[PDB]
Image (spheres, coloured by chain):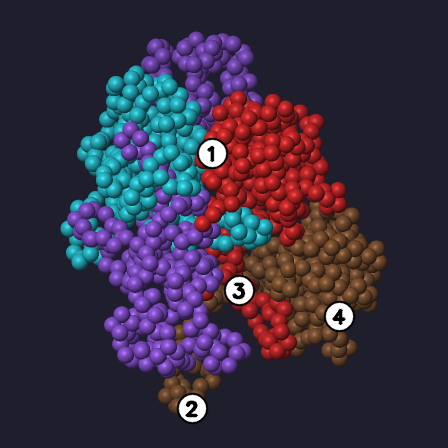
Chain colours: A brown, B red, C purple, D cyan
Amino acid sequence: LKSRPENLSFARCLNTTEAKFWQTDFLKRHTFKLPLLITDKAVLASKGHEMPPDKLEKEIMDPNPQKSQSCTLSTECDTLRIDFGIKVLPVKESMYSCSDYNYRTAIYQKIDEYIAEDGFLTLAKRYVNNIANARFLWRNRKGAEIIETIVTIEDKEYPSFNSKSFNLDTFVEDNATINEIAQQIADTFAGKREYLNIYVTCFVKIGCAMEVYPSQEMTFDDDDKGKKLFKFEGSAGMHSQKINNALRTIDTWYPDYTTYEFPIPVENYGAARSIGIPFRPDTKSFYKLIDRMILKNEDLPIEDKHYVMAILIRGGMFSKKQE
Amino acid sequence: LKSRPENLSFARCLNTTEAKFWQTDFLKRHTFKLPLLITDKAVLASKGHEMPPDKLEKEIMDPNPQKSQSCTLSTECDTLRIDFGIKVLPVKESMYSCSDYNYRTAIYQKIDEYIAEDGFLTLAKRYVNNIANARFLWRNRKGAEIIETIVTIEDKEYPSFNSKSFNLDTFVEDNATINEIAQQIADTFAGKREYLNIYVTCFVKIGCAMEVYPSQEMTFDDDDKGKKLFKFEGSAGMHSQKINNALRTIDTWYPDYTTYEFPIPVENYGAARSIGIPFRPDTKSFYKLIDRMILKNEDLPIEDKHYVMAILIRGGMFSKKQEK
Amino acid sequence: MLRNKILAAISQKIPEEQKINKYIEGLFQSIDKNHLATHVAKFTETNSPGNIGAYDILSSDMNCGYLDTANAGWKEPDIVTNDAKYKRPQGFVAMEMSDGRTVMEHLQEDSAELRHEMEELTDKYDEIRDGILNMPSMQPYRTNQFIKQVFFPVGGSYHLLSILPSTVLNYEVSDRLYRSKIPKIRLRLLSSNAASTTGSRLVSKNKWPLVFQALPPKFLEKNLAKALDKEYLLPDINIDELEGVDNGCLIDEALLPLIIDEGKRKGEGNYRPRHLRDERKEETVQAFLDKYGYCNIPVGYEVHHIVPLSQGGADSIKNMIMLSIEHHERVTEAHASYFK
Amino acid sequence: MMKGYILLEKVNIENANAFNNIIVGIPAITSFLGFARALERKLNAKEIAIRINGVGLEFHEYELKGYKNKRGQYVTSCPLPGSIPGQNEKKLDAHIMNQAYIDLNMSFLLEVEGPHVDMSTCKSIKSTMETLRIAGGIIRNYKKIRLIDTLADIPYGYFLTLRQDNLNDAAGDDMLDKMIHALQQEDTLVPIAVGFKALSEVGHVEGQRDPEKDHCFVESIFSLGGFECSKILEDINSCLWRYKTEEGLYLCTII
C-alpha cells in the first residue's frame, strides 16, 4: 500500500428521513393530531440596510415591499409534534467503491480491530445522547416549557425522556434506556445484526399561536426572490441533512478542546460554523489521520480511532488525484 | 481458415426493458400500487474536499450551495415494487453480420457441438439464479426486511421466491423452480423455441418514509452539475443496462478465482468497473479463446466453453483488427 | 507581430529561436499529411482507421425537394488530417494578423504583408504556399466495421450503402441555427481530446454544434397522467376457442383453476375506486345473448366477468362468460380471498 | 392476389436511435422502411410469399431520453459506454460519441400483395414480429394486429406526410435558407431525413458487411414533413411511404 485508491468512496450508515410537523394539545397528545400548514406573507419594511451616504441622502425614507412565508400554530393547540425515523446499517458492508483490493482488506482489518477493541459503544452512546437531549429541534428548542421524546423500535415502546434535564455540553453514560438502545445500535454497527429501524416522536410545548421554524429552502439566482419554507406532503417539515447535522455533534477530541469546551459536528477538517473557527486544519485532519492508519500502519490513540470511525459512519468522497 | 472475418457482429440474446417503481403496503401488495415521484433538493454544505494548502487555508470555512434530487417513500407505505420484463432469443439466429462464409459454418458447427454436449443448461441456471437472489436491486437490497420475487412466463405463474435466504456468492442448482425456468431458458437459447417472454415483479420491504435509489442519468450542461435521476413516464425507474449488468454476473471461472471468490460480469477481457484490474488480461481473454476454438480447432475445457458461450450471449463486435 | 503568436503557440523551455524553428519544422513535415474534405469519416467513430472523405464539389439543383452538400450556402471547405500529431497547419491556417483578416485572404491573394513575416522569420514560404494552395482531395477507398453499412432494395436486388457524415453542412447548420429562433438542441457531449482526435478542423473549432429539433407536437409527450389512466383490461383467453364452453355454458370443472388463475394474474395491482371504476351496463350483457343466440338468461346460470371490474375490468362483450350458480360463488370467494 | 391493409396497433419501442447528421428526434423513414423490408424477408423465408407495397406511420406518444431545462430546452442522456473495439480495449473508461435515444408508441399501416391474405397471415406476422428491432429499438409490447380495408376503423393518431411544396416555394437564396425560412413562418413542419445521395461510383470495396453486393457511398438527404389527424385524411393511399430508386438516388417518397 503506497497511496489511497483512485475511486475510494463510502455510503452513510445512519439513514435519516424527512420530519413532519403536527400540532396538538399536551393533555391529549396520545389521542389526536392536526396538520400544520405553511402560510404566505408579505411585508412592507423600510430601507434599513447599510448604504453609501449619497444613496442614503436620497432614499432613506423609502418603503420596501418584501415576500416571505411563515408557519404558526393555531389558537387552540400549544404542542408541536415531530415524527421521523432512522435506519442503521453495518459499517463494514457500506464501502461503496474501491479500486485496490489490498486497501479493502486493510480497511476491513482495521475495522475488525476497532470492533474487537471498543465495540462501537462510545459512538452509539453519543448518538443516542444527541437523540435524547433533543438537539434536532434547532431554533424550536428556545423558550419551551416541556420537551419530551420517545423512541420506538419494532413494537417495543421505551419510556419517555425529558430533554430539558439533559445538558447540551456533557454526555451521560449511566441512563438505563440510553444504554439499552445504544447496545442495539452498537450491535448493528459492529455487524452482529444486519439492519435496525428506529422511530422518534417529539412533543414540544411552547404556547398557543406561537411560531415554529421549519427548514428554509435554498434558492439560486434564476429562482424567484424571497424566503421559501420546506413543504413535506403538504405539511411543514425539516430536511434530512438538517437533522443529521444535529445527531453527529459528538466530536470532543479535537485539539484545543479544553479552551472552548463544547462538541462540534464531525466534519472532514473540523470546521464549525457556530463559532467560525477551524479545528482540524493540518495535523488532526481526517486525510492526514487515515494516511497514518493505513499507509504507514502506525497505531493511533483511541481518540483518533473514534474520530476516524465517526467520519466513516458519515461517508464521503475519499478519492485521489490519479497518482 | 486463417483469422477472424473483417466484419463479424452478434446481437444480445437477453433483452431487458426499463424498470418502473411503485410503492404500496406489504399486507396489501397484491391489490393496489401508488406512483413514486422524484423531488428536487437543495443543500448547503462545506468545503470538505481535499485541497492544496493555500487553497485550503483560504477556503477552509466557506459555504457551498449544491443542487440534487431525491426519491423517498410516503408516510403510509413501506414496500417498494419493481416490475419489468425480459425477452430471450435464440443464439444461432442472433448473429447479425458475418462477412466470411467458412467462419460462419465453423461457428455454427461449434455451437452445434456445444448444444449436443451440454445444452445451455448451466448458463440458464446461473441467469435464473442471478434473477432469484435479486441482485438487480443494487443499493436497494441493503437494509431490506423482506424481499419477495415472483416470475411469470407467458400465462403460467411460478411460485414466489425469497431472495434473503439465497446467498450472493454461491449458486443453487437443486431448486425445482430454478431448474423449471432454466429448462425453458435453455430451450429458447437452443433454438427449439423462437422467443421467450418473462415478467418479473419484485417486492421489497424497507420501512415507512425510507429512501430508494433509482438510476442516475449521465448529462452534460452549463452551470448545472447536480444529480439527475432517471424519470420514466413521470415515475422513477432503472436503466435497462443497469439491470442487464446484474443478471450476467455469473463468471466464476477467471484465473485466481479461489483468492477473490466472487462472481464478476462477463466482458471480453474480464474487466469489471469495481476492481480497476482486468481478470483476464491476455491469456484468458475471449479473443484468443475463440481463436483457439475456431482457427486451430483445438478442444478446450468446459469452463472456457461456458465463458465463450456467455460472451456470445451478451453480444458485441467480434471482428478482426482493422487495417488502414 | 506574427512572431509573438508563433512563440506563444510553442510551450517549451527552449529559447526564442528554437521555439521559432520548431514551428517551421512541424509545418514542413506536416504539409503533406493534411487533406481537404467535406464529407470526412471518423466523425461518427474515432476508431475508424485511416482517413476517408468525399470532397463533393457539384452544382446546386435548387429544384429538388431535399437538402445535401453543395446545395446549402456553405463557403469554407473542411481541412482534415489522419492523425492529431499532424495538426499544426490546421491551427496555422487560423491565425489573426494586425487587422481583421485571416491568413487565407493574404495567402491565395499573395499579399506581401504576410510575405514579410514568412520571409523574415525563415525562407521556405513559397514551397509551403505551393503545398497548401493546391491540396490533395479524398478518395473514399476501403471500409471498416465502424462506418455504418445498410442494405437498400434496388429493383429485385439489394445494394450495400456506406453512410458518411457532412462536416461543412453540420457547421453551417450550427451557425445558422445559432442566429435564429428555431427551438434547436445543443447536444454538448464531445470532449476536447475526442474532437482533436477526429482529425478535422471544423469539429475542433465547433465541438458542440447546434442541431435541429425534429419532434412530434407538444400534446404527444408521455407524462404521469397518460400512464396513470391508461385503459381497461381484457382477458387473453377467448371463449369460443376452448373445449367445453357449449356456446356460453361452462360444463367441465377443469376450467375453474384456469379461470381463477387468469382472473388473479391479470388484475393484480390494478385496484381503482368506484369513482374510476367502470360501469356494468345492460346492453353489453344483452348483446352477448343476442350474438350467441339466446333470448333470456338461462336458469341456474349467471354472468361473471373473468377480469374483475374492481381491478380494472372492461365492460365489453369479450370480458365475461356465463358460469354455474356454484362456480360463480367459488370464483368470487377465491378472488375475495386472494385480494382482500 | 388480393390487396388489403394490415394494422399493427400501439407498438411500444424504447431506446430507438434518435440521431442524424443534424437531426435529433424522430428517426429516419429509411429505418421504418428497412424494418418493413426485414419483416418481408423474414416472412418470405417462411414460405408465405407476400410483398409490402407502402408503409404508413401513426405517432401517438413520444418521449426524449433526457430532461427539459429550466429555460425550456432539452438536454439528452446517454448510457455509460462499454468496451469499444480497437485501441484501448483494456481501458476501463471509453470515449463518448454523439448519440440520442427516443421512446415511441407508434402504429403501422401496411399494404400487402400475395395470395389468400387472411387471418393466417395475421397469426404468422404475430409469431414472426417479436424478433426484430425498430430503428435499433427493442419492441416491448404491442396491442394487436388487425386486418382493415377502409379508413373508418382507424385509431386516433397523427400521420407523417411528406410536404416538399412548402420547402420549394419558400423564400431564400439556397436550400438551407429556404428550409429555415419555412420553419420560421410555419411552426408545424419538422425536418426529417428521407433518403440518400450518391457522391460516389459503384463497384466492389474491401471490408464491407457482405462482399458480394454492389457498394456505393451515400449521404442522408433531408426534407420537410407535417402531422395531421386520422379523420382529416382523405384517402387511405395518401399516407403510404414507399421506396424510389434512381441514378444516384435512394430516396423514399409519399407518392
* Amino acid type, residue under disc 4 in the picture: Thr
Which residue is under mark 3? B66
Mark 2 vs mark 4: give the one in front.
4
Which residue is under mark 4? A252
User: Do the residues indicated by labels 2 and 1 lie within the same chain of the protein?
Assistant: no
Q: Check the residue under mark 3 and report the chain it is in.
A: B
Q: Which mark is residue A53?
A: 2
Graded by Cα atoms within 10 Å as few (under 14), some (14 to 19) or many (20 or more), the crowding at tag 2 reads: few
Q: Check the residue under mark 1 and report the chain it is in.
A: B
Q: What is the x, y in percent for residue D169?
A: 15, 51
User: Do the residues indicated by labels 4 and 3 lie within the same chain of the protein?
Assistant: no
* Amino acid type, residue under disc 3 in the picture: Gln
B168 versus C337 height, above or below: below
The CA distance from mark 1 to mark 3 is: 55 Å
- On the picture, is D12 further left or further right than B146? left
C82 versus B303 height, above or below: below
User: Do the residues indicated by labels 2 and 3 lie within the same chain of the protein?
Assistant: no
Q: Quadrant of residue D151?
A: top left
Nearest the camera: B41 or D59? D59
Work out whether residue A91 can be spotted. Answer: no
Element class at badge 2:
helix
Which residue is under mark 1? B100
